[PDB]
Image (cartoon, coloured by chain):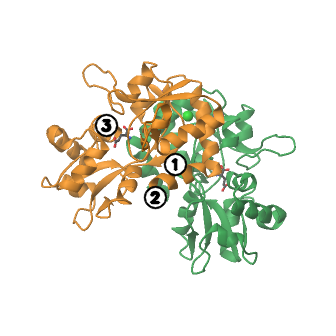
Chain colours: A orange, B green
Amino acid sequence: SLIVTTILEEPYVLFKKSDKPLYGNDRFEGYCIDLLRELSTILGFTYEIRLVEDGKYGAQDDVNGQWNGMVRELIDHKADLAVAPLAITYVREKVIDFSKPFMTLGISILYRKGTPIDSADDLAKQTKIEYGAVEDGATMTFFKKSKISTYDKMWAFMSSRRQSVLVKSNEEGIQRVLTSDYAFLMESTTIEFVTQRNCNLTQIGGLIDSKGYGVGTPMGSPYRDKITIAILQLQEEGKLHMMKEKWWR
Amino acid sequence: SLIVTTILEEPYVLFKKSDKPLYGNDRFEGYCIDLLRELSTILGFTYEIRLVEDGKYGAQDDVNGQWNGMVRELIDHKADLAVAPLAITYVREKVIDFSKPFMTLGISILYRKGTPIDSADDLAKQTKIEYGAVEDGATMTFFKKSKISTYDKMWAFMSSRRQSVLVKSNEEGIQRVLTSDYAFLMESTTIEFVTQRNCNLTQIGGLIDSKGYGVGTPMGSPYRDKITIAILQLQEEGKLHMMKEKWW
Ligand SMILES: N[C@@H](CCC(=O)O)C(=O)O
Ligand SMILES: N[C@@H](CCC(=O)O)C(=O)O
Ligand SMILES: [Cl-]
Ligand code: NA
Ligand code: NA
């Protein structure tokens, strides 16, 4: 059986609700759990889902250049696959492999409706409304590495207030938007899930970039290209779209 | 130096307009030519651009299983790369390799404005308005293979009328929409180029599927993963976005 690392993130991966105790893979449900099941149907592998220990997606540390999160688990061969909303990025592709994308997305802004804020630039040009992102994720890394003035300014702001504006999880960021004057830089796919359930919230502006979620594998894994082929089949059959419809309702 | 196969298709690849006759790589410009130039800078290769001889993207003969177009050029190792609006598909990924996508898109419908036609289903349930797609491309292949009722029905319509409703190129299909009661199934990226320039035309409905364009290589090529990393570099620095804005 393949060891599959993943992370709790609605509506991709969550704990299934039952009146009775649940065990093994049956504990989990969500878009990525359905994806994993479909991949196993096509490719014929068995698997064991395990939540990532540190609860992080994956980032490289400045000083010791060590990785954390699901990325680290693949690097160290503690997992065979990462099936999660894991963004395919330049720096990650240098240390792990990824299937082709099963979903495409971009960074955008989650905030309230009816305000004068209409873009990242509007946030960058002020300090009254705090804004931030998930710590040690692809969104934070985008801002940290950007040479675009607007985003460079936004990183300077977030970095100098790390403790107060960066959050541990999307759920924490979403809660901050709901309970304080705060705008959250996060992925558009997940924004769509939030805005269909919270009618006072909206995406602000467009997509700031473009990226895909892919299944992660250790570098050189033979499963990478097989999973790509299975994803392409599921897309063309209309199955990924049905799965998106099911979980984003 | 690498041999790069490609295909004429606005605004991805076109012949540069000029008074002085042009030679070799100078003959070409477009989104995909800019992409090729950026990839060459990052990876440090030189290249010769050659248009695909048979003028096709690539499909498999369903009797003997032989391929044509750019896909065939890669299979036969007649080109090192295909840099073009070449859709990454299940059937192609089994015979060639692709970089990760530099652009994402989906099949949709090009038609005229002001009608009650709002979806593929609306087209499928009638015959007065003819519809078709490019022969031997990914869009046609999607319909040919689909188990989805509506799309299976549309394939029955298109295949039975192959001579009259399938076209050799996007340009031919677009001209048909402009000059007759015809709706053209084509890729949303290319629709966007067209509707920005022809105000009487519009996309009908949403995306019917989702796919990306990738740089093609022969199976097992070491350039594949290198080009993926270069594409990710270009995306992250904002260049792919600037490239699309320039050509659209
Ligand atoms: N999906 C992101 C985490 C969330 C975010 O950074 O917005 C990643 O793969 O790192
Ligand atoms: N871009 C398509 C051709 C055009 C189409 O099929 O709509 C391909 O790669 O085959
Ligand atoms: Cl790949
Ligand atoms: Na890699
Ligand atoms: Na392949």
Q: Can you identify the residue that label 3 sits on?
A: A141
Image quarter for residue A64?
Answer: top left
Q: Point out the tag, 3 or 2, that comes first from the N-terminus.
A: 3
Decide: is B203 above or below A34. below
Label 1, label 3: how far apart the Cα atoms are: 22 Å
Could you say where residue A235 lies in the image, as x and y percent from the top left? Answer: 60, 48
Could you say where residue A176 lies in the image, as x and y percent from the top left? Answer: 22, 50
Q: Can you identify the residue that label 2 sits on?
A: A249
Image quarter for residue B176?
Answer: bottom right
- Counting the numbered discs, the total is 3
What's the residue type where badge 1 is placed? Met
Tell me: A37 left or right of A213: right
Q: Can you identify the residue that label 1 sits on?
A: B103
Label 3, label 2: how far apart the Cα atoms are: 30 Å
Decide: is A59 above or below B248. above
Say what secondary structure mark 3 lies in.
helix
Disc 1 to disc 3: CB gap under 8 Å: no
Mark 3 C-beta closer than 8 Å to ligand 1: yes
Rendered image: mark on residue B31: none
Q: Chain of mark 3?
A: A
